[PDB]
């Protein structure tokens, strides 16, 4: 573990936006209004 310091900075915490469509479980304070897609 590194307490995600690189992910939060050089990847701008993008895991939040991924969870906000790959999981979208809760929405009181975060992204929850999209779902997964594909072409194959």
Image (cartoon, grey):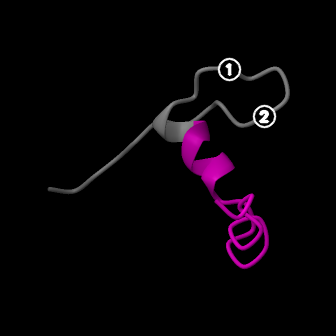
Query: What residue appears at the point 79 percent right and 73 percent down from the top-left corner?
Result: 9
The magenta stretch spans which residues? 1-20
Q: Is residue 3 left or right of residue 20?
A: right
Q: Residue at image x 67%, y 47%?
A: 16
- Assign the magenta stretch its main secondary structure: loop
User: Foreground: 15 or 36?
Assistant: 15
Q: In this image, 21 relative to 30: left or right? A: left
Along the line of sight, the residue nearer the viewer: 40 or 27: 27
Q: Give the number of the disc on residue 30.
A: 2
Q: Residue at x 72, y 79 (%)?
A: 10
Question: Looking at the image, is 4 positioned above or below residue 34?
Answer: below
| Residue 7 on image: x %, y % | 68, 67
Q: Mark 1 points at which residue?
A: 26
Quarter of the image with the N terminus in it: bottom right
Secondary-structure class at tag 1: loop
* Residue ranking furthest to the bottom: 10
Q: Position of residue 25 (x, y in %)?
A: 59, 21
The C terminus lies in which quarter of the figure? Answer: bottom left
Q: Measure the C-alpha gap from mark 1 to mark 2.
A: 8 Å
For residue 16: magenta?
A: yes
Label count reads 2
**Left or right relative to 18: residue 29:** right
Residue 31 x/y as whole percent: 71, 37
**Contact flag, marks 1 and 2 (Cβ < 8 Å):** yes
Q: Residue 9 carries which label?
A: none
Disc 2 is placed on an element classified as loop
Q: Is residue 5 above or below residue 29?
A: below
């Amino acid at each position: 573990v590194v307490f995600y310091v690189a992910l939060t900075a050089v990847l701008v915490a993008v895991a939040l936006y991924a969870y906000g469509l790959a999981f979208r479980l809760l929405g009181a304070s975060g992204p929850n209004k999209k779902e997964s897609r594909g072409r194959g």
